[PDB]
Length: 212
Length: 228
Image (cartoon, rainbow over all chains, first blue to last red):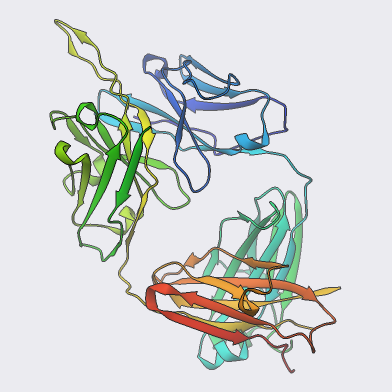
């Protein structure tokens, strides 16, 4: 059986947030909701559809109609930022089923454009017969970017790794992307480029083998 | 007050075996149904297995069917998980959880159970990798002459984690240590940067200290601007 949730959902503080849980004929089943803050124990917030455990705010409330169940948090606070999973029991397949989870972002600070720094392979690493380009992206908000690497003028996705954005010592976000070459490839092109895209806008830095 | 303590998470090669344990208190273990739920790092929750108070009902997820074995010992308030024939897909965070235990009877329809979680543990980490312990190589990310950025490439190590500081802890302003990426080689790599007064670059001296306890390695590297 399958439960599907929107991957992301954002709201401005004090407003009201809605998280959907898609399952077919899900109104026939009891739906429960857990909240999980990064590096921590999940926590029951709504059970048996609309019921709520004592010890959690009256702001959390539950719906379940036909093909879609809904966790509704009102007067959202900064502390309500977490991941939310819905759950059921499939009597048919003998399975507990969780949904994908929804990361609820509370736009509790000013937007911020990413600052990008691109390092070429150090003489040292090269001397070890490996070449690595390091693209460091920091101080942006919200925490969702896109990286793309170009050689000379044309892209390539062979040998790229990119981290998932992550808060820093100031609630802003930062991510990294490495491009792995062989020293041969490194000095055989005129230049390499890192291209970060953040909410519509695109920054780009470039390095060339020949230089600093 | 409910308390659950997983243990025995570790690192193992594919095909290998491992036995997680979980220790309860603050509720009647004897009356309770238990669960194992796992969570791929970064990804979502995935139910693994459940088991009723006496072992009566026990079910497994298709993924682990035939490889995993759930068990308990009520005399010890203990839940067990036996993972055999491990895969890399099994690498994750393993949670043990208690179930409220809500049921329902009806003399001709049988019993009906309504499972869902009532308490969780902290977790325990299970890594399945073909690779074995290896200390990191450390390379300088030299600044390329407002302010400037310089850093450390911490390359090809295993298992996690590495920790990085600068100037033996005395530099924290401007410092960010990223998450690690896991490469095709099954080895981890991460970086650390610090942004600094562009001017104070020929004078002030920057050293990063890498520590990798799994291999008892510790490295210090001074990062100096290049030469051209």
